Image (cartoon, rainbow, N blue to C red; front, side):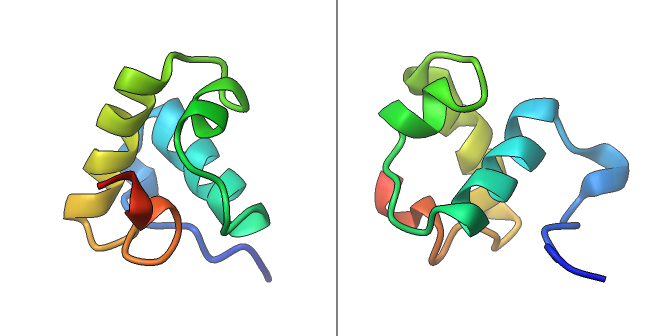
Length: 66
């Protein structure tokens, strides 16, 4: 019905799915913030987002994280 951030939901860490939901709600957020909206540090927040990157789900969202 909306969102569309399914990605590997059947197997997605709470940090990645919530991070994808935050990227869709905010396609202009880096990682530091991307680290606090999910309740984690950014160093790893990226580690979480990177996992979402390898699956081709962060080429526009926080793709900048690279």
